[PDB]
Image (tube, rainbow, N blue to C red):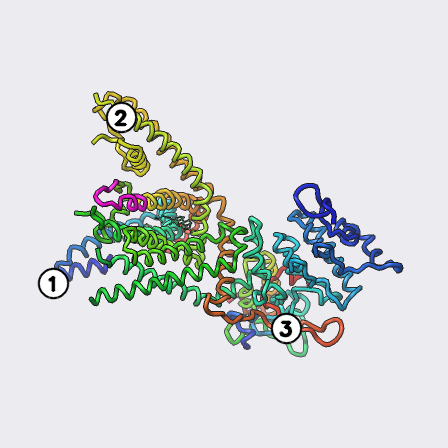
Amino acid sequence: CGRFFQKHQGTCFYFGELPLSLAACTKQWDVVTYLLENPHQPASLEATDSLGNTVLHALVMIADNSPENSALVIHMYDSLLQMGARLCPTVQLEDICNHQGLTPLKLAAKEGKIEIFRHILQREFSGLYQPLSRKFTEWCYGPVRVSLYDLSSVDSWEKNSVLEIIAFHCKSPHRHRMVVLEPLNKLLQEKWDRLIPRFFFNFACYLVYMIIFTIVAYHQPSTFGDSMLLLGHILILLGGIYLLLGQLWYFWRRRLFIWISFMDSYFEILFLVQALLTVLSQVLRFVETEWYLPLLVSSLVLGWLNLLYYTRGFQHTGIYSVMIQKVILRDLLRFLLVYLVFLFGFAVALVSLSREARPVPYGGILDASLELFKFTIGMGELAFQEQLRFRGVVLLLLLAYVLLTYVLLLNMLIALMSETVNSVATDSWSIWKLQKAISVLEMENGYWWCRRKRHRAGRLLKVGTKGDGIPDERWCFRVEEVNWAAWEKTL
Amino acid sequence: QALLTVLSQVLRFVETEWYLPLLVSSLVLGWLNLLYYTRGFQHTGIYSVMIQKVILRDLLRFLLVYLVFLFGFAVALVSLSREARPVPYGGILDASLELFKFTIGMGELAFQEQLRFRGVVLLLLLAYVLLTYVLLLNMLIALMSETVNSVATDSWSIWKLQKAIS
Amino acid sequence: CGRFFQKHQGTCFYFGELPLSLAACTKQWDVVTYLLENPHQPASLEATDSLGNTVLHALVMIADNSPENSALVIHMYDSLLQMGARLCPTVQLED
Ligand SMILES: CC(C)CCC[C@@H](C)[C@H]1CC[C@H]2[C@@H]3CC=C4C[C@@H](O)CC[C@]4(C)[C@H]3CC[C@]12C
Ligand SMILES: CC(C)CCC[C@@H](C)[C@H]1CC[C@H]2[C@@H]3CC=C4C[C@@H](O)CC[C@]4(C)[C@H]3CC[C@]12C
């Protein structure tokens, strides 16, 4: 456990700080056998390091997304697992918990590994070493294949599953491709199909609440009507506090998720803000302060815009929302910065001028900035102000501002939006798949007041007998597929 | 169009005041129906097919989001603007019409000093302008560009099928 | 005409519910000849199923747009038509 051996930033190379792990990680398929079959002092394959990793953990840590590195990692992983089958058949090397509490499959997901993780998720072996496999084939009748994928530690029925690690714990920039591979993709779609009624019931309840919000905010004073108004008032106080409690529970449960993915939620912050503003407005109304209506109407705007959360759940409109977000993030803040610099330079210049008399426009900085923004809209006034003999300077400044802003910046913004939308069309689908995944994982749990029963997804299949005694049964996931390509090579 | 024309002609006999709207709606629809006979030529028929595909794909999502923005901000502006320290934003229809005027290019963005909620109204109007005029319309142009680029290849075969049906 | 053999949504594989159609659809160019040239009990190539499809209908139903599937389907279609030319020249299997 040296500094040069520990995994950190700088001069380091982590390999598990064990001779067997070092031999396995360096593609030496000559001495690994001798490290176990030496009669004088055999080594234990299930040995662990100070950090808590084993040889398989060491192998998955060194994995990258490079093709050669993947070839090495899967080759050595399979070979070492096969060797472990022949040395200690009783104890399995697959289930060895780290000090963090992660198996090799979960470590492949948290660390952001995509090539070794995919192979572990779908691996097959021949008749010998059959039990140490994930994907099985039930029957190959004709050209239709029935694949059984093992759902060990990947279904959300357990406490810390792979699906909860990809969607909440992985902090890789491009984890959305991890939730699109076959096994997981057939599972998430089925879970989503099972959860359509709950999603749309939540949407309907929120829509009714927002309609009540609009009704109470509209029909309010500058009796029976007063009774209904008070009823709606208290009802919306309760609704706001309910939303606040739900969002607070979400953030308490995901305290370490905001740092990991801060632009992947951006709807829980908005919901929390809306609920907080509603509660504050309702409680502040009692103080009879004049700043009730602005808070109420700001909360109303935010609530009516929050339906874009429930926008996703459909194929096209959710991808549209994802593209909206990506356009907002990438090519809208640079343009805003440059445009604001231009605006607040020219406004100051016009305010400095225009007091040279040979109401008056460009009185203050706010008025000049507003006029220039009117130029941006399409309602700006470009007139030859003959009142003051600095006519030419004002006209030339206005024309230069128009040329630099209306012609350059907005049209170039349209061009940049076109480029961004063209570029991110491919990734837009996978990001929306990940959004469904997060929504489904939230929906498997109940609310902050009710606990939904865990509907264990999967089927118990006769996969054959374990290596010692009577048959071993594991919960698999069935998928039928038609493939003429792999059927021609079995006959 | 034919049903509306027949209904308008028969309803004229009843001397009901709702003859002219039916007649003029039928007239609009009939004059737009010539886009059927548009196809039959190489370029203009493919143009019509592209028009249809643009309408179907990237015009209903934008319409949905734009309507949500519009009818949120209109309600918010109607709720405000009665705080006197005709008056604009009287009803929901008037506020929605003003916001659509913003969409056109004829919207009025003025510093209403009549009522001391000046700042809130100005900030809501500016936020609506930023979210709609700058984001949504330009992004719509971008999406139309992407769709037209994508479906240029299939546009010819669809027009061939249209000739086949004709 | 079983549920697993009928073409529907779910667990199914339609092949014409006939032994000759099954042999033709599975790329077995060894037993199709024997299904017709057995002296004891020959089979009729123009046989039809309960739904009404024949062996050529069964072949075209299993066709997809995949290249390997197309290669199989056209190969067996041509071979079976050529065989039908040499067995019952009077009656055509196309119609
Ligand atoms: C509060 C009023 C006065 C000003 C507007 C501030 C709010 C509404 C702004 C700040 C950030 C903005 C959001 C940022 C993210 C997105 C992208 C997509 O998901 C739909 C629009 C949406 C959700 C925006 C809606 C408007 C928004 C929520
Ligand atoms: C009736 C008036 C008041 C409102 C307009 C409603 C009608 C005209 C709308 C509804 C659907 C629209 C049509 C939808 C399909 C197309 C695409 C292309 O083929 C030419 C335009 C055309 C034909 C549109 C013309 C206008 C249209 C026909």
Of tags 1 and 2, the one toward the viewer is: 2
Please state which amino acid type lies under the numbered disc 3. Answer: Leu
Query: SS at mark 2?
Result: loop
> What separation in Å lies between label 1 and label 3 (alpha carbons)?
75 Å
Numbered circles on residues, count: 3
Tell which subunit mark 2 falls on: A
Residue that numbered label 3 is attached to: A461
Please state the extent of the stretch shown in magenta in the rendering.
Answer: B110-124
Please state which amino acid type lies under the numbered disc 2. Answer: Ser
x and y, in percent, of residue A309 in the image: 42, 56
> What separation in Å lies between label 1 and label 2 (alpha carbons)?
67 Å
Residue that numbered label 2 is attached to: A354
The residue lying toward the viewer, choosing from A372 and C81, is A372
Point 32% across, 26% down: residue: A397
Please state which amino acid type lies under the numbered disc 1. Answer: Val
- Specify the label residue B14 is tagged with: 1
